[PDB]
Length: 50
Length: 198
Length: 36
Image (cartoon, rainbow over all chains, first blue to last red; front, side, top):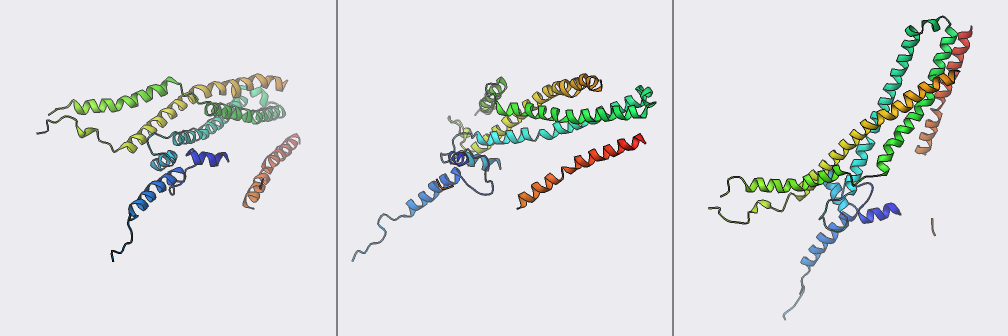
């Protein structure tokens, strides 16, 4: 539980240098993916004038 | 690797400050890497003591050679004393090494001086840049300050801090270990040898 | 509310402790031989 809390707070004893993990990956997702999804969403996606 | 460790230690919050977990991990690893030299020094001391004892028995104590049984008894007694004392020295060295890790002195003046020098380095560089053939380009607010290279600066600061801490630890070890070695593996052994023989 | 490799390695490490016993036996045998 202490190790999990440390990983949550970014104080993990060991860092997975192989790939992004922990709080850093969570922040990267919440920023990049969220921004891309918001930009890609069409405010009026789908309309028919007729 | 340093950049990845810094990014991971940043956590959910945006990267705006130098993480401390990575520095602690690196300094702990560096300190742990210093354990093997202590064992090598202990082994060298033990070998030197054995060689000195053998030389004394061979030359300085030729009378003891007249009684092979007595010489063998003395040799085995000394060897057993060294064997039983070596764990004591090893555990004392381990405790001395672990004391520094257990208690971290963040108020040491050396760390404050290093931090001050690191902070003043940027100001010195800016002054040097702005004090060398100042000006077509006669416009204020130079763009020389820039905004990138923050990660490189943080990595350099971390490396300098780690090197300074490693040097301080090495100096402390060099100053302390000889005293404990002399107190335990030499002085105490010499004092107790006569008592054990009697 | 709700809640072999290592075993072999530790067994081998424990078995390796017989070196001290062998050394002690060798020393005792050498001491006995010195008497004769």
